[PDB]
Image (cartoon, rainbow, N blue to C red):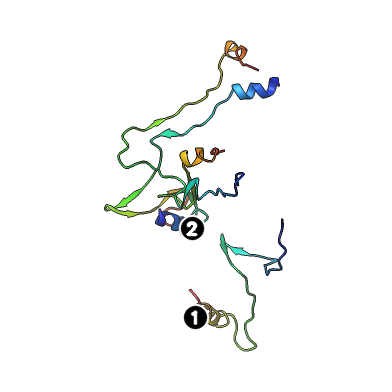
Amino acid sequence: KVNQDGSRVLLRDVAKIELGGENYDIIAEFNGQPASGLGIKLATGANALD
Amino acid sequence: DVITAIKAQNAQVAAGQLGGTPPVKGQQLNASIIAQTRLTSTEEFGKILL
Amino acid sequence: EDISDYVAANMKDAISRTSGVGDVQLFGSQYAMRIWMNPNELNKFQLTPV
Amino acid sequence: FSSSRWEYGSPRLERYNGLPSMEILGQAAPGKSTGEAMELMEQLASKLPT
């Protein structure tokens, strides 16, 4: 908004804006060291070792 | 006006949680919040204000 | 937060769409433009999260 | 309330496997074929920007 004054209101003011993390539920520690992993789950009747 | 007031009263809404995903370091309790819930009987539907 | 974003924005897409993968449960989450509202700096300008 | 500007843009953007990728079509040579025509092309891309 703009008020009846001239003073401008923009997101920056009303809210803190940081980039990253769409959800904060799961975090991983590789030997205590912060890390992310790729956990692949198998299909049904696939080809394993291949 | 009958329809519009029906879905306004007979509603199931998903609200947030006490002590959510990004927390304050030292948060003790984590609980889900229930706001409105779906009306279950003929009496509760009779009490829908217009 | 920085790693789990990168592993999704460089690696995950190539996995989930390859050799007979059922589903890839990645460890973390990719970035999102998070808008962390403040109710007081929000009340001050007669504004709402809406 | 509007501004009028001329600006360059692509009429045909193309993507290979979820990543932005432009295609180049070529030949073998009147002498050599594929096995070397592809081989020299392999590191013409390897000897340029990261």
Residue that numbered label 1 is attached to: D47
Q: Quadrant of the C terminus of chain C?
A: top right
Callout 1: residue from which chain?
D
Q: Does B3 appear above or below D26?
A: above
Label 1 and label 2: CA atoms lie apart by 25 Å
Regarding mark 2 in the picture, which secondary structure is present there?
helix
Visible residue check, residue A43: no
Q: Residue at x 53, y 48 (%)?
A: A11
Crowding at dot 1, Cα within 10 Å, few <14 / some 14-19 / many 20+, comes out as few
Q: Quadrant of residue B2?
A: top right
Q: Residue at x 35, y 55 (%)?
A: A35
Q: Amino acid at mark 1?
A: Lys
The numbered dot on residue A49 is none
Q: Does B14 appear above or below C4?
A: above
Residue that numbered label 2 is attached to: C9
Labels 1 and 2 share a subunit: no
Where does the image place residue C13, in percent across and percent down from the top left? 51, 56
Q: Amino acid at mark 2?
A: Ala
Crowding at dot 2, Cα within 10 Å, few <14 / some 14-19 / many 20+, comes out as some
